Amino acid sequence: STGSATTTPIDSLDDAYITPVQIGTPAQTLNLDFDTGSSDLWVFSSETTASEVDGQTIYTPSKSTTAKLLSGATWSISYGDGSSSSGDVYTDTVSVGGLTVTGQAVESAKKVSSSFTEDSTIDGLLGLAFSTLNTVSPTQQKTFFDNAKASLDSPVFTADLGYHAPGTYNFGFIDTTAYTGSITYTAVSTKQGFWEWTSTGYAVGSGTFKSTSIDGIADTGTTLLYLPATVVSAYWAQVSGAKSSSSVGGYVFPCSATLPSFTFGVGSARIVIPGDYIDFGPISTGSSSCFGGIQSSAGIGINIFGDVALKAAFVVFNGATTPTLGFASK
Image (cartoon, rainbow, N blue to C red; front, side, top):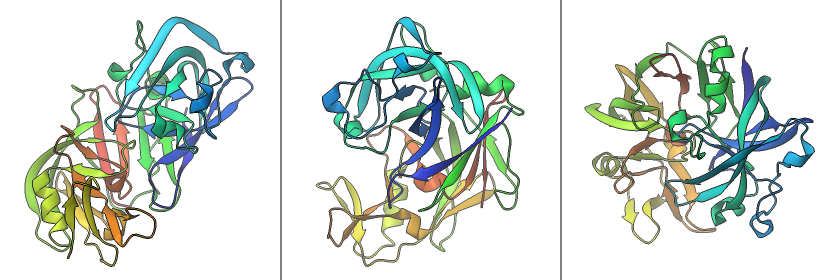
């Protein structure tokens, strides 16, 4: 089997991407944030505290003839940005782009933190990291991909995120029309539950490539590119007037700037992030200070190849017995 679904930016800055997902019988379609950095499929629901729902579409398990309470199961997750959610668990039928999993754990939110409430466009998360990170207790549950994998034509999914435009998540096949040149594959460590890999270095603009190992995670659920402070400083030093602002919470730059590209290495191959991908717009409405898309990972504790990086590539999440990651230009 295979599946193919379009993923769409939630706003004009590509702050996140949503993908329609069918849950239950009859189908209830929710727009979920596909997140290769976590492993819970959770949704706003009829059980979510009313004051914490503000415009999201909810899953109502009582209206699904295939929903079953997973008795005694609870979940609770906290993400790197301090956001969180928790609740109980149903199993139900879940379909993405024509690919169907029966008995998928659908984690129903009883509580969500303020940033989730405040984002009316995201109805939940669909985790695509390794199932070892799943938070369901006392019986850990599998991700949608883990459940689908054996049925897929090939045990892979691909992320093809757009810049200020829709893109595609495919399951079970590699669309050879969706990228240019060849796909370069690179090793993955699953030890921390992430799609963790090591970039071979970077360049800023037309500058020379610096060969240096950068361990980090391929994370569609993080907006920006978070890298070591040394790398980030080298980038922003090429932008007149750019500075790290403690009050704003990262590097800002004059909105009048033309940003340089940023290149990262994948083995001997190179992925080029155009300068415009690194512009996240005014820090507040009407400001001439703009927020940068490349930020320091210092104090996160891990480097993160988030959407800013991934959207410059066609990315293969290869779930073979020994997982690997593939990157192609597009």
